[PDB]
Image: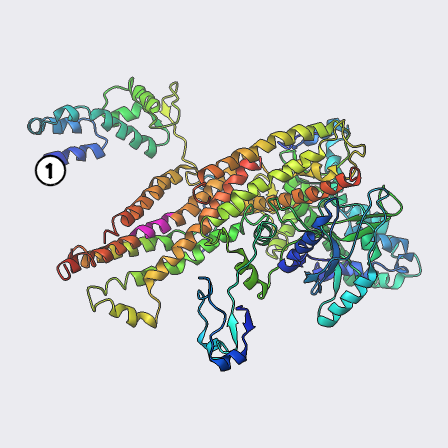
């Protein structure tokens, strides 16, 4: 349920606990720009590809 | 005690014209004058100056003269014509730190408590900032003399002002490096300051001229810093200093990869903005 | 600046025009109308001037004023430069959403109209190349200056 | 004496170089960090210490020769990496 | 496309005589298009696709198991393709020829390696070219 | 001593120091000396030198206020024990990197489980950070993952270096002017 994060072992029951906020801000907030810009080049078809 | 000094370009210039006016002596003269200014908020300010009559004979070079009546009345005029202005200390033209400047400062400290000096340049060639200033500290201390006193450099820069920025930027009208973009840093401190580090590596090479042949006082308090520099020489390339360096190249270049991707689309939208003005006028105009 | 010098009002009474122009150097700078409302040119005249410039001084105000020492051999707030590389890019998404908006209302009302109309609000198109210069030189300088200290410092 | 490459000595070497047992060198180096004569870190399970800073001492006319030659090839390294910049970014500013 | 699309269906799989089930069904069609001499050598590329496929999936696999899955009919050269897989450089890790298992090391931090910058530097310089070509092809008026 | 740790305690030792007439007691001048300085002798080697002077002198009644009500004493025997079992754990976090579980319990002279209850209620108090183990007995002090602080502290060392190479340069050029000026 991700309320806690870790790992469970089956042989002897060892809970290796670790933590890091990895990164989220840098890539996916720059990834959605690419699919915004894809729709801009799609909208270039409605004033260039049809027109000239 | 003092954070830093602030020098205007007027007093920077107001020594050069006097260096021209005594330049007809030919043989030898240092320009020594009274430095005026108003230090506030623990920051040293320098505003105005003149120069006092001063001569020097080489045999027994401990004989100086300051015509204090010229110092009394002209400052009294300057205290009249600007009561905001006061004395801040003195200066000298400073090629090479002449010997009388150990007691010139002690001659006229009965006016300014922190009677600061300023060493300027008359023949400019460097890669740094050619204005230098010291401060007076004294010591009954470690090894040298019972009466010991050595000058210490407080950092120096040329302050600007809204009145004089009008003047100097009209007075330049010359080769300039404006339009700070991706290139001004490349030449103000990447072309230049790497060669600025030359003359500091080569400066301690010049003290190194005493290994068995140079001057007779040897080290004692010069090598504690030089022992530290090879000690504080940075970390070698074995640790995650390798790995976390590739980490941030793998982050900083992604922003450049996005930003360059945008640059191609924008000019392509500009390309259609010229194909709208090419085809839609050759039938219209001809 | 415009330095002046008087002319005789006695010759103003004579109606006689002074100063006997013998060189093609005076009538180069034109006077302002506001100075022409005043005594120019009925009691004084203008003088063309320039400035005496020399390596004695010109070299030593250029190579003395705008100079620095460490501002560039140093890094820049290393945990926050990469953080500032998101403080711009985050709204650059939605600013590109406006650029995913404004082109779509073209093939429309005669874009000279799209100059006068858009003066209340910010356009994407000019603002969208504004940060691209900023998101470049902040990165290319900071990447290059870090990769020289690896060579020079051990 | 050790170079700046490692300067990472072990507790057994102090047991050799000071002929003192293992259960007292940790009490020794905690004093040395407290006085301020040395600045480093202490591991206990791998039996090593990462000394970083040592107190500056004096030296004669021989150790300056070490600071002579170690300084001298650092001149050309500042020369060599800058020589790219005045050659590759030459047209960017004359 | 349907005979030729059925060919690359066999390539993305790891089966070996699936190539043979195509090359008898449409061996005559490929000679009409005049391309058979390039088709016949895909068996080198089928087996390097498969040995990359198996080594990435299984970590510690017996060499006397990979041949039965690739229908190789021989374990005694099942060592030997893996030798040419390392000689070409497909998989890195070692083979316990005494035991029989082929162990593989788990991958490590490929993010903190230089190689994604090489995915960038091809495309940084390429995307500045098309911005330059958009400038060079614009101001004809 | 008995106060919990604070910045207010960190100069409380200075406010009570600098006193000409406090140091007339030779014992109690050393008491505050022990807690300004380095690691303390464990608990038993101190009470054999200082758990006996609380009767002597002409000073016994606040020490009788320690001794007399034994439940007040039990609150003050153990809180004096609490500050000195803590005084190790401050500086062992500061000067060590990776110590074994058996080694720390030996410098506290108590059970290894009793050591774990001490490090439990201090890091849920988060006043000493630690990442202990109960399989290898390997604990470590001030060990985060450190993604960004490597190159950040490296960039700090450049600026400390570059500020120092400017210190010597304008200090050599005057030193040549006091031997060969004229």
In the image, residue F167 lies at what x, y percent? 69, 45
Q: Quadrant of residue D59?
A: top right
Query: Residue placed at 84% from the left, 56% from the top?
Result: B107
B242 and C11: which is toward the camera: C11
E26 and E123: which is toward the camera: E123
Q: Quadrant of residue E58?
A: top left
Q: Is residue B34 left or right of residue C44?
A: right
Colouring scheme applied when the structure was drawn: rainbow
Residue at numbered disc 1: E1
Q: Is residue E122 magenta?
A: no
Q: Residues within 10 Å of mark 1 (few under 14, many from 20)?
A: few
Q: Residue furthest right?
A: F58
Of the 4 image quadrants, the one containing the N terminus of chain A is bottom left
In the image, residue D17 lies at what x, y percent? 75, 27
Residue range in magenta is B257-265
Q: Secondary structure at mark 1?
A: loop
E113 and F83: which is toward the camera: E113
Query: Residue placed at 85% from the left, 49% from the top?
Result: B63
In the image, residue F128 lies at what x, y percent? 63, 52
Q: Is residue F66 visible?
A: no
């Amino acid at each position: 349920d991700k309320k806690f994060h870790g790992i469970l072992d089956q042989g002897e029951g060892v809970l290796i606990i670790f933590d890091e906020p990895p990164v989220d801000k840098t890539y996916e907030a720059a990834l959605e720009t690419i699919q915004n810009m894809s729709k801009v080049v799609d909208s270039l078809y409605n004033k260039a590809k049809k027109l000239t | 005690a003092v954070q830093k000094v602030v020098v205007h370009p007027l007093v920077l210039l107001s020594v050069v014209d006097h260096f021209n006016r005594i330049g007809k002596v030919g043989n030898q003269k240092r320009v020594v004058g009274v430095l005026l200014g108003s230090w506030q908020k623990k920051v040293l300010d320098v505003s105005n100056s003149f120069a006092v009559p001063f001569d020097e004979d080489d045999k027994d070079d401990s004989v100086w003269f300051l015509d204090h009546d010229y110092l009394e009345n002209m400052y009294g005029m300057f205290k009249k014509v600007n009561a905001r202005e006061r004395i801040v200390g003195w200066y000298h033209t400073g090629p090479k730190l002449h010997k009388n400047d150990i007691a010139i400062n002690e001659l006229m400290k009965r006016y300014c408590p922190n009677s600061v000096l300023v060493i300027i340049d008359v023949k400019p060639k460097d890669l740094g900032l050619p204005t230098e200033a010291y401060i007076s500290v004294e010591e009954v201390h470690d090894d040298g003399t019972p009466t010991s006193k050595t000058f210490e450099h407080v950092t120096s820069e040329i302050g600007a002002e809204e009145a004089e920025e009008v003047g100097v930027e009209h007075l330049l009208r010359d080769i300039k490096d404006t339009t700070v973009g991706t290139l001004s840093q490349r030449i103000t401190n990447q072309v230049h300051g790497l060669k600025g580090l030359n003359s500091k590596l080569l400066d301690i090479r010049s003290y190194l001229e005493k290994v068995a042949t140079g001057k007779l006082p040897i080290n004692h308090q010069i090598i504690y810093q030089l022992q530290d520099v090879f000690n504080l020489l940075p970390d070698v390339s074995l640790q995650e200093f390798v790995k976390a360096f590739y980490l941030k190249t793998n982050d900083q270049m992604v922003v450049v990869y996005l930003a360059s991707l945008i640059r191609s689309v924008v000019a392509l939208h500009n390309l259609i903005n010229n194909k709208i003005a090419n085809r839609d006028a050759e039938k219209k105009e001809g | 600046i415009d330095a002046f010098r008087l002319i005789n009002a006695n010759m103003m009474v004579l109606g006689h025009e002074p100063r006997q122009t013998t060189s093609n150097l005076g009538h180069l700078n034109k006077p302002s109308i506001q100075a022409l409302i005043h005594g120019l040119n009925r009691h004084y005249y203008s003088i063309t001037i320039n400035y005496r410039k020399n390596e004695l001084e010109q070299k030593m105000l250029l190579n003395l004023h705008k100079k620095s020492w460490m501002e560039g051999l140093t890094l820049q707030d290393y945990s926050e430069h990469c953080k500032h590389n998101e403080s711009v890019v985050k709204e650059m998404l939605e600013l590109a959403k406006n650029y995913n908006k404004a082109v779509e209302e073209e093939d429309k009302m005669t874009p000279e109209q799209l100059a006068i109309k858009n003066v209340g609000k910010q356009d994407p198109k000019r603002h969208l190349e504004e940060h691209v210069d900023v998101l470049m030189t902040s990165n290319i300088v900071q990447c290059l200056a870090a990769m020289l200290d690896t060579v020079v410092f051990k | 004496t050790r170079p700046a490459n490692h300067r990472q000595l072990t507790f057994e070497e102090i047991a050799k170089s000071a002929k003192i047992t293992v259960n007292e060198v940790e009490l020794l180096v905690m004093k040395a960090l407290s006085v301020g004569l040395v600045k480093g870190s202490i591991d206990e399970v791998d039996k090593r210490v990462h000394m970083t800073w040592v107190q500056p001492r004096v030296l004669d006319l021989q150790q300056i020769k070490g600071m002579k030659d170690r300084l001298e090839f650092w001149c050309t390294d500042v020369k060599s990496m800058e020589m790219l910049v005045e050659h590759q970014a030459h047209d960017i500013l004359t | 496309l349907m005979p030729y699309f059925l060919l690359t269906q066999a390539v993305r799989t790891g089966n070996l005589a699936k190539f043979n089930q195509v090359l008898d069904q449409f061996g005559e069609k490929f000679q009409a298009d005049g391309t058979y001499t390039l088709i016949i050598r895909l068996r080198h590329n089928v087996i390097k696709t498969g040995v990359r496929m198996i080594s990435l999936s299984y970590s510690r696999i017996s060499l006397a198991d990979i041949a039965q899955k690739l229908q190789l009919d021989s374990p005694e050269d099942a060592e030997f393709i893996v030798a040419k897989a390392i000689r070409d450089g497909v998989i890195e890790a070692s083979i316990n020829h005494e035991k029989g298992y082929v162990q593989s090391k788990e991958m490590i931090d490929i993010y903190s390696t230089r190689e994604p910058q090489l995915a960038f530097h091809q495309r940084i310089s390429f995307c500045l070219d098309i911005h330059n070509m958009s400038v060079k092809a614009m101001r004809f008026p | 001593i008995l106060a919990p740790f604070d910045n207010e305690q960190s100069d409380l030792v200075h406010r009570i120091s600098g006193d000409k007439k406090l140091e007339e007691i030779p014992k109690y001048k050393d008491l505050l000396k022990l807690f300004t300085t380095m690691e303390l002798m464990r608990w038993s080697t101190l009470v054999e030198d200082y758990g006996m002077e609380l009767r002597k002198g002409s000073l016994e009644s606040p020490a009788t206020d320690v001794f007399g009500s034994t439940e007040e004493g039990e609150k003050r025997w153990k809180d004096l024990k609490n500050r000195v079992v803590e005084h190790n754990i401050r500086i062992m976090a500061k000067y060590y990197t990776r110590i074994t579980m058996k080694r720390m319990a030996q410098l506290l002279d108590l059970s290894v489980d009793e050591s774990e209850a001490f490090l439990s209620n201090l890091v849920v108090n988060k006043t000493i950070f630690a990442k202990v183990d109960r399989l290898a007995g390997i604990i470590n002090f001030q060990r985060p993952k450190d993604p960004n602080n490597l190159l950040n502290d490296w960039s700090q060392k450049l600026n400390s270096l570059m500020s120092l190479v400017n210190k010597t340069t304008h200090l050599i050029a005057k030193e040549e002017m006091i031997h060969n000026l004229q």
